[PDB]
Image: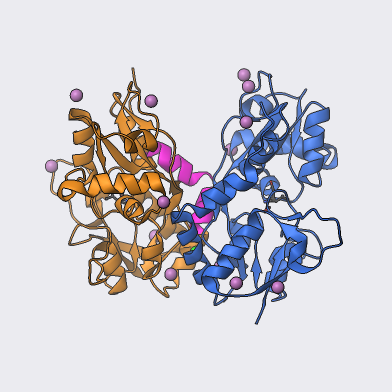
Chain colours: A orange, B blue
Amino acid sequence: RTLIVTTILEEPYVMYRKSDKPLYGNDRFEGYCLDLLKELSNILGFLYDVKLVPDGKYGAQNDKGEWNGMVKELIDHRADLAVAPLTITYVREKVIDFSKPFMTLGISILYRKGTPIDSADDLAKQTKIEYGAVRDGSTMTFFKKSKISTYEKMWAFMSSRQQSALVKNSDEGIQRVLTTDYALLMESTSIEYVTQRNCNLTQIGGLIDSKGYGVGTPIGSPYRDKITIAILQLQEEGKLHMMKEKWWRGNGCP
Amino acid sequence: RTLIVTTILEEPYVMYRKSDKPLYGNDRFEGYCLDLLKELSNILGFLYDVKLVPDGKYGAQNDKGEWNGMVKELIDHRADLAVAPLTITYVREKVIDFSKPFMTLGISILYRKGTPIDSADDLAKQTKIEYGAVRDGSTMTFFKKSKISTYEKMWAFMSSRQQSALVKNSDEGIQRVLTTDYALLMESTSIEYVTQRNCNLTQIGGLIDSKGYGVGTPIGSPYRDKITIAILQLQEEGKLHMMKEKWWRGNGCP
Ligand SMILES: C=C(C)[C@H]1CN[C@H](C(=O)O)[C@H]1CC(=O)O
Ligand SMILES: C=C(C)[C@H]1CN[C@H](C(=O)O)[C@H]1CC(=O)O
Ligand SMILES: [Cl-]
Ligand SMILES: [Cs+]
Ligand SMILES: [Cs+]
Ligand SMILES: [Cs+]
Ligand SMILES: [Cs+]
Ligand SMILES: [Cs+]
Ligand SMILES: [Cs+]
Ligand SMILES: [Cs+]
Ligand SMILES: [Cs+]
Ligand SMILES: [Cs+]
Ligand SMILES: [Cs+]
Ligand SMILES: [Cs+]
Ligand SMILES: [Cs+]
Ligand SMILES: [Cs+]
């Protein structure tokens, strides 16, 4: 059987390969998520067809409760699997199925080395350093929904001034941190990838929560549980950690 | 109708409450897993009867391949849920359904403070300091099945003299660490709890793998997905973190 896999460009999970000529089909892509998909397909014995989500989004709900992104692709049975850094969340888990996590992480803070900022409360209690998150992502949703005082304060700040503190995507966020006085609230695995490559940046504080990425399937799909068992096998064999080290490790920080 | 919940005594997850009279029913018990069970039952709206697993085991396979412990209670439909620090593993996930994790953790090392030992490699390359794990637990299985060179060596040591380096339970392991030249390979969440209470002990190195604890249900359970959603809600609200802080915090160490 050939499975249709929805995905999205996101370093280092899914990237365009480098080549002298135009590329076609699955050969267009490489990354952690392509390696994962390869291992899963060998364990479970399926073939696969990788398609970028047409609207370029992960999956959030609008005011009318309608979904977009890779989540909507699954709800509508336009894909068999979503393989991406798709955060397992309460709201998504109500409308699609996820495997157990293939990576665990938490929200943390990307900012410059060598400053007095130590934690999110240090950001919450001031207004000179701007801070925000990718608009409509699981990090933003976390803050919008929080009832913890510090995070309520932070949400009030991020959402002020027509959400001027938010960014459209992680790359925009990375550039804003590098150039201006701005902190990005970012999933810790992406932070690790960034700070391997930008020696002037650092994670600030630890993880403010705990969550995972999981393979998405339509609700009621039989592949959800097979993929879970396959992920646990890869985890216990040390394969997922080897895959992470392959794609994360940078060129060293002087 | 009332759900039967299998569990096991294990500090600080499930413990006998302290009282001046004999205790009965759910009132016998307190701890992280009792708080979790309460929260789950309020979200999902069920009543429950907590029942200690009769053989006092978590769940492992005998040579015939028949299961025991909480895992077997679920297989046999003698319990509806298992709420305990029941590690989510490849072998278990084949025979029962686990919620998504309510806690994430890894194997690490419990040892004495003040020594030059820094990692599992340091242990593996020597014979003066003994080391082991709880017999037939998920940590022992990790070493038993590892194809990583260092962990193969460590397993060879752990299995000599008919497994004399292994212990029957965590308290025996802790007492051996306190009294003799011995390090215990232990789940990091249990190391955190021990080292807040025994000031001469410390965790050595970081986590050598990654995994979670989940709520166990029989394969096919109408509650598995409902419980996963409730866990996600409790995580996102900061309630699991608060519960961990309540039960882990000690006031005596350094
Ligand atoms: C790359 C981004 C936009 C994705 C990745 N996982 C989160 C998601 O699945 O919503 C988003 C990041 C975030 O919200 O910090
Ligand atoms: C307390 C012990 C016997 C349990 C706890 N979780 C692991 C399990 O579920 O197998 C075991 C610990 C270990 O093997 O380090
Ligand atoms: Cl699951
Ligand atoms: Cs090219
Ligand atoms: Cs294949
Ligand atoms: Cs679901
Ligand atoms: Cs700092
Ligand atoms: Cs509050
Ligand atoms: Cs700069
Ligand atoms: Cs209840
Ligand atoms: Cs009861
Ligand atoms: Cs299962
Ligand atoms: Cs050393
Ligand atoms: Cs040390
Ligand atoms: Cs080997
Ligand atoms: Cs302490």
Q: Taken as a whole, is the magenta stretch helix, strand or loop?
A: helix
Query: Is residue A182 in view?
Result: yes
Q: Give the range drawn in magenta.
A: A230-247
Quarter of the view holding residue A83: bottom left
Viewer-nearest residue: A34 or B20: B20
Front residue of B178/A221: it is B178
Considering the image in quadrants, where does the C terminus of chain A appear?
Answer: top left
Q: Which residue lies furthest to the bottom in this view?
A: B1
Task: Please say whether residue B43 is one of the residues in the magenta stretch.
Answer: no
Looking at this view, is A162 or B78 the one in front?
Answer: A162
The reply to whether residue A168 is visible in this rendering is no
Image side of residue B68 versus residue A3, left or right: right
Q: In which quarter of the image is residue B28?
A: bottom right
Left-right relation of A178 to A139: left
- For the point 56% across and 42% down, the residue is B209
Residue B27: x %, y % from top left: 75, 64
Q: Which of B72 and B112 is in front in this view?
A: B112
Residue B105 falls in image quadrant: top right
Which residue is depicted at the point 24% across and 50% down? A9
Report the side of A161 relative to B161 (left or right).
Answer: left
> Is B148 located above or below residue B212 in the figure?
above
Q: In this view, does A24 lie above or below A172?
A: below
Quarter of the figure that contains the N terminus of chain A = bottom left
Location of residue A35 in the rendering, given as x and y in whole percent from the top left corner: 37, 49
Q: Position of residue A148 (x, y in %)?
A: 42, 49
